Image (cartoon, rainbow over all chains, first blue to last red; front, side, top):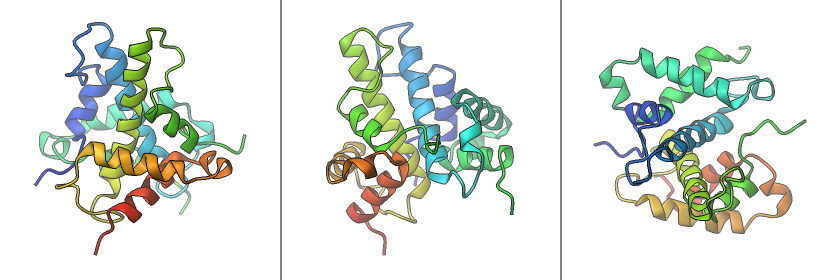
Length: 100
Length: 100
């Protein structure tokens, strides 16, 4: 019943530099791994900007990764097995809420 | 600047083509990092919208998503490709793999 490309656990591993399994090079596993996490987060952040979270023009990419990493660190194993993107949306919404 | 998005459509199209990692000097590594970014950006959008904007995640291979998105971005004029990539990914997925 898993159909998602990244789980929360895998996105957390990507941020930590651990999600380039098909890369044999060392000390360039890290570059590919964090490129995946940054780009996955960017997909969710770009799509949801101005709807689920606000202030895209005043937030640096590194700040998005930091908030998401903190949030994923808060999640128990059952939530981290679910799709990563919903967790990114939740992190952005609590971090950078839109005025209701 | 009016632009707040991390990837434009033009940048996602360049990433799929292996040309969005300018601070990576080894050519093969530039290509690997670039396509890692495109795959992960698309995955963020695809995972978030699965079962709502597009359907079939269990049966469609990741490479098929990239192929449909690349075709779709190739359909867009330059002004539209300057907009956020994620909404273009959602549009590509919705026309390619519609729900109900």
